[PDB]
Image (cartoon, helix red, strand yellow):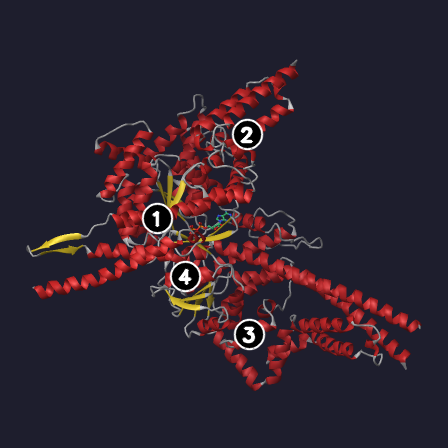
Amino acid sequence: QDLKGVWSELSKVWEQIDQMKEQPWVSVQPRKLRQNLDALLNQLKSFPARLRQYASYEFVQRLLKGYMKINMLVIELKSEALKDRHWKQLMKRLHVNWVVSELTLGQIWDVDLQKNEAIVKDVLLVAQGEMALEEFLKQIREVWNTYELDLVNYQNKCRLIRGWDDLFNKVKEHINSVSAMKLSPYYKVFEEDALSWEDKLNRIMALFDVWIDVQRRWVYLEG
Amino acid sequence: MTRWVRGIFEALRPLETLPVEGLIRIWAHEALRLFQDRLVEDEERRWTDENIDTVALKHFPNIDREKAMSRPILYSNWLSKDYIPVDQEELRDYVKARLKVFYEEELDVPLVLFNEVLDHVLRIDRIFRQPQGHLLLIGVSGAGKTTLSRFVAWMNGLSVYQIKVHRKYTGEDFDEDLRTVLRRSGCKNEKIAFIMDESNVLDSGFLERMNTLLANGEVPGLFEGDEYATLMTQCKEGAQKEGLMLDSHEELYKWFTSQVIRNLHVVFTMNPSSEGLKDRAATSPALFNRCVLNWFGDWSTEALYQVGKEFTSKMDLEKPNYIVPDYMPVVYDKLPQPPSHREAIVNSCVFVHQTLHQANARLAKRGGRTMAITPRHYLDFINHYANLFHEKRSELEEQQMHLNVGLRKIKETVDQVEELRRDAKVNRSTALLKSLSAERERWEKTSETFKNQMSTIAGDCLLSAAFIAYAGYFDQQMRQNLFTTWSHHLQQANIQFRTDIARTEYLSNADERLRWQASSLPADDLCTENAIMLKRFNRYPLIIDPSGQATEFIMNEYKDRKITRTSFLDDAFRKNLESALRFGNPLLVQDVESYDPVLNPVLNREVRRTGGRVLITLGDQDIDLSPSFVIFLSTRDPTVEFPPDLCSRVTFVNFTVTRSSLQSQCLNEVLKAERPDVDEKRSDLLKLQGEFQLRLRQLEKSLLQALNEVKGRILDDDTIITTLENLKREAAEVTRKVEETDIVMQEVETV
Ligand SMILES: Nc1ncnc2c1ncn2[C@@H]1O[C@H](COP(=O)(O)OP(=O)(O)O)[C@@H](O)[C@H]1O
């Protein structure tokens, strides 16, 4: 009958949804997921109105609509922000015990992301701040490890250093930024490396501030 | 004319069938968006509105003018598509829905969508929905320039990005910021709505680079060296993303440039100033050539009245016994007749705003120094009104509850003493009953007075808030004149308020005044009002004073909270701000003339509240704002000018002595030093506004505390009646003061 047909269609839709949800979170592409779920919604709309009036079809349709609404949550979650510590905070606050290697879209979808939108957004903002500071530190290492002194000849006698203004400006901006980074609640992570780089910056600043005077005096007295 | 042509063409492209009335309607709308949009005052706007219809009827006879040129001319593509005309009300409903959604994501602060905002949103959208749609907004501070810009940018997918300026802002930081915004806009192909205020425009170095960026679509010299090589590295990836594989450097550079034009819109939010506008025309023609400009200055009367209605919804303002007065003093023409209590109050608020514009214009005509008045002043005033109404209503409500509990306790005690009588002592008990009954009728009279205060509370709070938020820059005489003007306007409204209200006492208590007097603060009426404002404010106060008493006064007031002193000239100012935000200690600031734009997020109260955290954006860093943080701005030279953007973010506290402040000071000194008795009578008249009632309330609380222990021991001589006859004698004294207030007031006036 019509009830048997709608039950069979519902079983097919549930099987398709379960097969999609077996994809692990690592390999779930948000764009392809959205496209395939839109295809599922189009397939659901292709049912006749008599089959559409059934309550179970409405429940599955509204579940897919909620998946549409939380798709942007999924997009923000699948990025370089969560890493593993933010995932740990999410599991701690949501009181769910998952496995990172075995994490799949089904486990996350079971937990109501729409209900927990505020928690997810807070975790995402914390991760945004953490990744911003991490990339700032990465820029620090990449700019100080590859930086070279501007060596220049001095009448075939020695090889002196120029470019004092640029180096000193970089050091001052760097030390001010590192000192200001002590603010904000995000400062609690990677504090030891921050203080180590503080010490490195202070050391280079003092050494080169002495060096400029030494070089100027040496050039004058040599002349 | 060419923009007119292009707009007509774009509006006609998606349509296939269109009557002539629709064509002339599109024509009129496009002309309004090109010609009437840039006009300044209302006369030119009316001239354009009438003459466009005149031209349309003169060149197009035999057409119906109602459909061809309808008064609410308005076009959009939000509802349905194809740029079809939209009705005002359906558009208002849609923008309300989108604003509520926005409230969910960003900028939870309420906004009121009146007709002016409804027009500006569509104008901003129309300019944004166009390649190379650089735009310039001109309007008084707080008119809703940046707010509407960010709203439309969010609604269109434009990711708003505004640079932040501070002192010692070198051109290299600016160049890096442009590098970042161009990399985000072109290489990564995200649309950006680039926004700024006038504060970062004042430096002329940035205007050259912006001129090149606006005209050419790309600034040469910003990208060079290894930065240019990196730019090419992600430019190739961006070309790969769009499937536009190219290898030659210059073709990819042109592709990046084209991506910049198609995906970058610059918004200039700037304060109307004829001389400054001429200067920026001189130094940058692209601001008028490439950047279409929008005018919207002070809110119209209808906008102010709508804001007043929306922001006074939680407030009660419902008097069923409100008698409508004949010849209502009205400033809003569409006021419902007869108006209700809330309508009358909002009309009075709009009247206060307009009459202070009138007073400012009159003072400017006199040749004095004036400060720009902004709708942010109106918002601050309505916030003071709401807060004061809520606080006073609460205080009266707990006072009435205390009175009711005391009356119930008195009834219980009377019943207990009657039961004891059921069992010289009898005479003492009868006297106790007589005294208890007498004080019971006295508390019924106190309830009557409480109801009268509840009647007058609305007017009292309105006057108090209007004084605190609006006045403060003017001298004592102008403050008194404005207060009298408001009082006469409200008495013309038959609104209930005290005819002899004292502003100093209705807004503070005895303990705070004595605490102020303990600190360095002379006993002057102007000084008391200024300290009143310093106690209660929403926008952080700005202090002007020549002798410096205010600085030491607010040091002594906040010494316990480790207040610190730092000026703009000192280079440690930014670090002191960091420390103040981290810890929460107050920070007085001097030398406000050399203003540092770093305080703008602090003054604007740009707080980001998410996940149990409150964040404030100083620089490119987010800082946890301490809940108990407060900042005071001070100066020393009265004859200074402030940019109106600053004037719209701080409340002015003026300590400069004038021909009226010193006159009052000398008169009070003579009264206290030559006619003392008149001085204590004037003090009694002034302190009758609750302080005597406050002492009565405290002593009645003590009496209730003593009477709570009533079992045998209270009858040591069957007469604990000493406390209640004491209460009776101060009650008789204050009552005699109440009946004889007019005679003493007249005598003080004569002296
Ligand atoms: N239509 C409105 N209704 C209610 N409040 C508004 C409206 N428009 C603006 N506001 C308020 O006024 C302020 C506008 O400031 P803004 O115009 O952004 O300053 P600036 O123009 O200097 O950038 C905002 O804080 C907002 O809360």
Secondary structure of the residue carrying tag 1 is: helix
Ligand 1 within 8 Å of the CB at mark 1: no
Q: Earlier in the sequence, mark 2 or mark 1?
A: 2
Secondary structure of the residue carrying tag 4 is: helix
Disc 3 and disc 2 on one polypeptide chain: no
Alpha carbon distance from label 4 to label 1? 23 Å
**Circle 3/circle 1 CB separation < 8 Å:** no
Q: Which marked residue is nearer to the observer: mark 3 or mark 4? A: 4
- Residue neighbourhood size for the residue with mark 2, other residues' Cα within 10 Å, grouped as few (<14), some (14–19), many (≥20): some
Alpha carbon distance from label 3 to label 2? 62 Å
The dot on residue A33 is none
Residues B348 and B545: in front is B545
Quadrant in the rendering for residue B16: top left
| Residue tagged 1 | A136
Residue at the image point whose x is 43% and y is 71% from the top = B545
| Residue tagged 3 | B515
| Residue tagged 2 | A65
Secondary structure of the residue carrying tag 2 is: helix
What subunit carries mark 4?
B
Alpha carbon distance from label 2 to label 4? 47 Å
The answer to whether residue B589 is visible is yes
Residues A150 and B725: in front is A150
Q: Looking at the picture, which amino acid does disc 3 mark?
A: Arg
Q: Which marked residue is nearer to the observer: mark 3 or mark 1? A: 1
**Residue farthest to the left, as pictured:** A156
